[PDB]
Amino acid sequence: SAIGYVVGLEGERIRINLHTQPGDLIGFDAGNILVVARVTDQIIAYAIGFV
Amino acid sequence: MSLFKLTEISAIGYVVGLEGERIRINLHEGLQGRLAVSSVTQPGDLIGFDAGNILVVARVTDMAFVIPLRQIIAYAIGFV
Amino acid sequence: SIYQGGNKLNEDDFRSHVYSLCQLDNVGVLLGAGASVGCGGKTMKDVWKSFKQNYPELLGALIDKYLLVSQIDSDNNLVNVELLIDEATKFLSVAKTRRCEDEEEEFRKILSSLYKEVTKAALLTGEQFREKNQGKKDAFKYHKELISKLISNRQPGQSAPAIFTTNYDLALEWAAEDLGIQLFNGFSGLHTRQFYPQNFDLAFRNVNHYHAYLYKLHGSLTWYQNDSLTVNEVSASQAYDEYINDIINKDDFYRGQHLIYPGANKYSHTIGFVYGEMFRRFGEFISKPQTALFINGFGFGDYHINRIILGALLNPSFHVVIYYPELKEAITKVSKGGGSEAEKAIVTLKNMAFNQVTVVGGGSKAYFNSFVEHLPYPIVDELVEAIANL
Amino acid sequence: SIYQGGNKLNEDDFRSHVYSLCQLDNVGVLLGAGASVGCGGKTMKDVWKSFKQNYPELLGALIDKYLLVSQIDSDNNLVNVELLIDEATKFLSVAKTRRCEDEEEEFRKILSSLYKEVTKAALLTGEQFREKNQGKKDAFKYHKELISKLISNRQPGQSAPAIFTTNYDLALEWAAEDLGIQLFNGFSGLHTRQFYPQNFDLAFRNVNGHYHAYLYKLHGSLTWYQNDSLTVNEVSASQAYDEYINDIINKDDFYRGQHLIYPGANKYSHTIGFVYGEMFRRFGEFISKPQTALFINGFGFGDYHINRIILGALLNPSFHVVIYYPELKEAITKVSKGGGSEAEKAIVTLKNMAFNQVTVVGGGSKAYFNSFVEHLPYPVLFPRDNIVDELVEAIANLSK
Amino acid sequence: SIYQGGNKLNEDDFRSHVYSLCQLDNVGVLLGAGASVGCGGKTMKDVWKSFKQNYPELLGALIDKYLLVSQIDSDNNLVNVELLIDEATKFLSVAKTRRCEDEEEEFRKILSSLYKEVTKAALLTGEQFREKNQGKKDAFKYHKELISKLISNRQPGQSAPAIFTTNYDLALEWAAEDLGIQLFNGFSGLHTRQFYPQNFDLAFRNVNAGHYHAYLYKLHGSLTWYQNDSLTVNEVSASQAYDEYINDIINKDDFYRGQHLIYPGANKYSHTIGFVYGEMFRRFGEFISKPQTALFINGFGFGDYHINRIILGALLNPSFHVVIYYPELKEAITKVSKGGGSEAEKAIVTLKNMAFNQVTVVGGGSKAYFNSFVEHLPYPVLFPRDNIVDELVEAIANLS
Amino acid sequence: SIYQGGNKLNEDDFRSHVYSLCQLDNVGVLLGAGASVGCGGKTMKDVWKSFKQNYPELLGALIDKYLLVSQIDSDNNLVNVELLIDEATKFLSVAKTRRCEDEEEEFRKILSSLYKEVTKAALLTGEQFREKNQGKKDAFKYHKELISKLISNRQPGQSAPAIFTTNYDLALEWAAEDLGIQLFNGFSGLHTRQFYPQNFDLAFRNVNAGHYHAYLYKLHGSLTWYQNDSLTVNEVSASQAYDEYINDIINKDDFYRGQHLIYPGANKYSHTIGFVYGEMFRRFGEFISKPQTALFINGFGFGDYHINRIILGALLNPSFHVVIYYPELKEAITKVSKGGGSEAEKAIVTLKNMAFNQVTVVGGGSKAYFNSFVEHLPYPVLFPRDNIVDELVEAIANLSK
Ligand SMILES: Nc1ncnc2c1ncn2[C@@H]1O[C@H](COP(=O)(O)OP(=O)(O)OC[C@H]2O[C@H](O)[C@H](O)[C@@H]2O)[C@@H](O)[C@H]1O
Ligand SMILES: Nc1ncnc2c1ncn2[C@@H]1O[C@H](COP(=O)(O)OP(=O)(O)OC[C@H]2O[C@H](O)[C@H](O)[C@@H]2O)[C@@H](O)[C@H]1O
Ligand SMILES: Nc1ncnc2c1ncn2[C@@H]1O[C@H](COP(=O)(O)OP(=O)(O)OC[C@H]2O[C@H](O)[C@H](O)[C@@H]2O)[C@@H](O)[C@H]1O
Ligand SMILES: Nc1ncnc2c1ncn2[C@@H]1O[C@H](COP(=O)(O)OP(=O)(O)OC[C@H]2O[C@H](O)[C@H](O)[C@@H]2O)[C@@H](O)[C@H]1O
């Protein structure tokens, strides 16, 4: 499944383009590393760490 | 044809515009692998441009869209 | 132990690297005698050991009277069984030309023995060599996957894969026939098959179904030459009925300039023409842009292949992956004075200074079966037996 | 001797007509049993003669008790062999159900003996059938010319020629292999060769050639056999001779399903035959395309299916046929006197049509296979103007 | 009881599955003799009872002398009726050819009784067979619904529906002539009707901008087909056939001509009659070998080896779908589980046990009948479900 | 005596056909050992005749003991030099391997005296080989005419002609250096000339916007090339080569040790280090695999297996045309019909009997020589007309009677 994709990066901010509320966590498949993010407010998210 | 060969360069893009301390770069798509070996695909990195006499050092700030096209914004900090 | 220019890598990075390489323009594979040992094959050391303890009554003549084999190599089991046959053929031809019966009768036994040992290890199925559907068995299970996920990966508009082989057994033909694809090897016809070099530039299309290429660098069991100065090809059953059956189950007989395996009769201008074409095609393919090469089962004991491979690394778009099992055992001998030419060559590539050579070592971790799994992924029987029941 | 549209035609116009008919989109040929007489073949009359010479007691059993063949018809050699095998099979099937053994054996003998004579006439070289390089001999001289002329009259963008046949012999294959051209017949592989219906849609291409054709054998081949597993395999000539042909020819073994061929009238008796249907489907798909030409040679017009298909193809106003029939005049006479055989009526009916798309050629020995190949033209490499050169000779007529 | 790959699903899922299968590239229907029992027909086991109740003297000579039928099959009413007529005709032909005078009358006396029984069960209207407008009765109400539903859900640029049947009655023709649709069956003409095998590749079009036609393949013949004195096959109307040869068969007691009729699968040994039978099977085999085919089976008893072999081999294609109706699943499952029953039961249970998502089997007695089969098919939105024409027609008739 | 597709055609049609073949995209020519006979050269039969009458004891040792040459073929002059060289090398190999000493030294004399006669026959001028302006003589007129006719017929935007040869002499470079044309052969430098495979793709260009050039391929080496110990091929001039390493070969005896590279043997795949030979044949095989290609063959005796195999397999392309010159066609036809004939005679007869209009064979004895071949080529037409009024003049010309 999926909820969207990434369209741009601005400093330390992530923009997600929709095809579910503040505080939820999301993940991005980057091959050898998985990146976890936190929703703050298209939606915006920040970064916390990697697994 | 003969022994002499000159060009050995591995670039990731070329300058497409200047707007008063603001640089736009269009990223190559035909490069199967940008390995020469360093990776610069993230804001906060350092890149350099060759101008024959000096090398200009810059810093990446933004990435965005618009086989789509990708763009990069950077700012200068000095030269070597 | 996985190295890249002296560094080290883990499993996941290599598994991503192999996937990245498979999406290039040109892809090829080179096999050896070690890739057929899982189906009933043998190696050079094994065949030499079998020869030593079966015919010891004439091994002295090869060292004393004629000087074809070295004592140290014989004791250490490091002989090359390909050059010896060519030298024996030259000796027999000269003796026959000079009309020396005594020496002529001596050389018809050494060849009759050597061919007898060589041919036995290549049947791969005993007396079932003359039957049909031999590629449907479980022994030939991993050979099919290689073809299946080499053809599938290629996008529309891409070229066809290439397979280079040093074996002379029918391991890659039965599997391809049972899969349902066609291999181009340079022959055409049914009632009279002949060698046409220019068939290597053909491809299929649809009027409104895939293929590959197969180059044999040392010959095959189904190739021979008749009274007419042309090279023919036959099937397994016809070959067994014609000449293969008598070689194994008879005491002593020899034909002459008849067979084309393994690299035997190179002094005839009709038989060297077919050996030269494969080498020139390999050389032309190795020097193309955006190419990859996977090597498996190769002992690095051939002088010319090493020269060809080394000279092709002057270009930046040539990638090589090697599977050598006894890596550390070679480094230990390199530390001391002794060693061998193959070991010296292989250890040199380990100490290179660029990210193009990738050597993979270990124990069972680098065999043929392990190599197949690294490549990316791509009910009839019930209906068949139901119809047969009716 | 030449009729087009029911009216007589001369030779000079015929040659020009033939030339312009080889430039269309689709061209094909159909060859019968008379086209292999210049290589060593035999017709159906010779089979009957050999059978009545070699087996004198089975003929008497056929004529006296079961009354399947009349004496006067046998004397004049005017008996049809295809219509006797069906009756023999019918008698055997009836006799096997009611459990009669002595009458059952006599028909197995007849069928085996009759198949044996049919097999002997399809080798063309006797005991040399198993050798190699049989296409280098002088007998197969005009087959190579036919293949070359057909394969050379093809502009880029067009389709490859198609050849249909009803023989069991390996004449076209022998001629083509000696020439270097590859033919497609539906089989693939070397160690295990099998039939694949979707292999008829393949074609060559150049990676950076253009010389091939298709072959359809409508009535089977002498090197094919079915292994009872709903699969058909193909072997070489030497392998077949070593496997089963020698036993049939020499050891007088009782006949079994060693090789699948179709001698007989009703071809639908064999229900599990799925090659005949595919072949005839491909044949029927050919004659429904616009801008098509077809040449027929060596056919006696004695098969219901083929001349039933041909008649329905003349309803398309882009289909042309040329028919070679030697004994046209003798067939014309016997129709006005009351009527001849069923084979002599179809050709007269075709001749008397009123469309300019049917051409019939007769004349005895000048409607043969060798004469047919000579009428085909060679391609012109570099064209000319013909306006400046042809007026050079215009001066001569006024100064001579 | 509904199975799809060995698992059960409810009615709503089955209806949803049926809806999705009706919008594919190819759609076909194959019907049997059980679909005409609601119009006045009889099944195959209701004819043997009548034959062995009305003619108890020939039955002994048909078992003890010629061995044409087994005692076990006769006692349980499991005799293939259409597989006996062909053998009887073969016996009669052999006896006539070899001139056994005493054996001709016996086989002329049993065929006269077999035809008299098979013919009377296919009229469907008794003596109202020569009249006109037979499709207006209430017995043929669901055939019209099936035909209308098949046609009225095809988008432009798509193929036309095909119908295969093992019957030889005139139900579908009567149903189609009332709606105004035209069916193609391979014949053309009015004063001399003839069989043309090439007219199966034709379609209609409008010269101004209709698409109202279908194909009907009859696999065992028809009541209205016969072979005249010549070698051709003709078709006539119901009244002409009744006045020509049906009345004598039903009424007269000593009437038998010879190789005249073409039902059911009788005179296959003649090469001008079996040619008709072969084409239908060939075109049936050609249809189900297409990429996106869906087939519905109803009324069939699965007693034919050739059709089963054809269907089984066609399932090794990942885009072929089959739906089967058999209202006796439980009585076959128990018998196969205990010791094993008849061949049809074994075939159906083996096909049910397959773990594919392509095969679906429906049982349940009266829930899997022909009448229930229609409602499972979708109904078009724009089809007029009202009555407006009849009132105006009656008002017009009332005038004057 | 001219055939096209097995039939016969006359002279006017042949000339009209030849004119049209020179207007195609790709044109080339392959020359043999008989094309240099009018300059001073000689063939292999003359080499054998010279050998037999200067080294009699060696011939006796060859016939009596080792049984390499028969007694009858020596008198009738049917010996083949290439096979003899290959057999001598094969004998020397086993002599070295078994460490026998006397026979190893014996075979060296034969193998060294056999090359000397080959080298002497490729000078074409004797003692004047080490001199300049050799192309001004009247013996090189037809070579110059051939080069001029080949170069002049090309249209702008087309490719340059290609020339292939199997001779060691310098008859074709001397002619070109007298006209001013530049020939590319894969070498660069003056004080040190080396071989580079990459410079076969070079062409001239004018800076303000030397337009005539061609290519030369030497398949069996050259008399001026030599290999140093560094496994590299170098080139010198005629005078330097004569004064440094081909004056001791002739006047002094038994001094050949790989001095200059040549391939007089039948099997040329034995040498597994030579890459010039493999480079030339790849270019040859690539040329005949293009559409709209024409080839002329003159002086070739059809006795090489590799070339014969290449030519036959290139006839399956419907855009390839060849013309073959052969003087003794009638004798070959007569001798093959008796069931015999040499291997060389079968190849030419097989080609003559094909049914394709893309093969033409020219015979006739002296009518198929080099001078006739050069004379059959056409001259360009510089200013053509639409020929719609000139043809009217031609029609009006002669009708006063
Ligand atoms: N199960 C195995 N899986 C993978 N590799 C294996 C295995 N077993 C052994 N090996 C490796 O595979 C190697 C096989 O060694 P040899 O068969 O002598 O090498 P070749 O086939 O190149 O030699 C023949 C050709 O090479 C010469 O030029 C000859 O003239 C021939 O042309 C072992 O040493 C192991 O490293
Ligand atoms: N040299 C010749 N060239 C051409 N035609 C010739 C020649 N010599 C004779 N003919 C003519 O060739 C014809 C040969 O007559 P038949 O052998 O019955 O021809 P078929 O192949 O149709 O019959 C064979 C059966 O095989 C299948 O089973 C079909 O059912 C066929 O019935 C005559 O017209 C000769 O005049
Ligand atoms: N009202 C009904 N509605 C639907 N199905 C019914 C009904 N009544 C009975 N059935 C079912 O209808 C079926 C009765 O089948 P039968 O008419 O005997 O067999 P066939 O028509 O296939 O026989 C002809 C073929 O079989 C020969 O072997 C030849 O090969 C022929 O091709 C049973 O399933 C009944 O339960
Ligand atoms: N004046 C002439 N002009 C043209 N052709 C001539 C002339 N005189 C003779 N010929 C013909 O020239 C033809 C060839 O004479 P040969 O010396 O046998 O040629 P080859 O077959 O050895 O081929 C030469 C090389 O081939 C090998 O690979 C070696 O490298 C050889 O050096 C004969 O048919 C003559 O009739």
Image (cartoon, coloured by chain):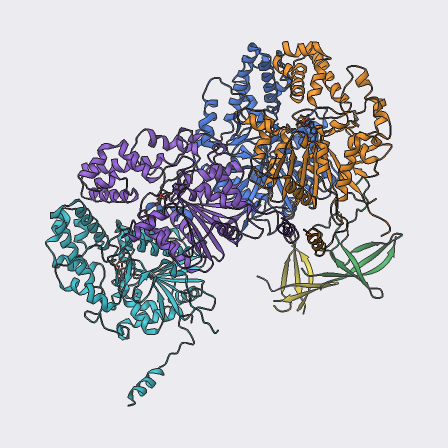
Chain colours: A yellow, B green, C blue, D purple, E cyan, F orange
The answer to which quarter of the image holds residue F74 is top right
Image mark count = 0
Q: Residue at x 60, y 21 (%)?
A: C84
Q: Position of residue E38 (x, y in %)?
A: 25, 68
Q: Position of residue E295 (x, y in %)?
A: 38, 60
User: Is residue F41 rendered to the left or right of residue C104?
Assistant: right
Residue F273 appears in the picture as rendered:
no
In this view of the protein, which residue sits in the foreground, C268 or E336? C268
Q: Residue furthest bottom?
A: E400
Q: From the viewer's perspective, is residue C209 above or below residue F119?
A: below
Q: Residue furthest left?
A: E57
In this view of the protein, which residue sits in the foreground, E348 or F50? F50
Tell me the quarter of the image containing the N terminus of chain F.
top right
Q: Position of residue F44 (x, y in %)?
A: 69, 22
Ligand 3 appears in which quadrant?
Answer: bottom left
User: Is residue D10 rendered to the left or right of residue F78?
Assistant: left
Q: From the viewer's perspective, is residue A37 above or below residue E86?
A: below
Q: Position of residue C177 (x, y in %)?
A: 49, 41
Residue E221 appears in the picture as rendered:
yes
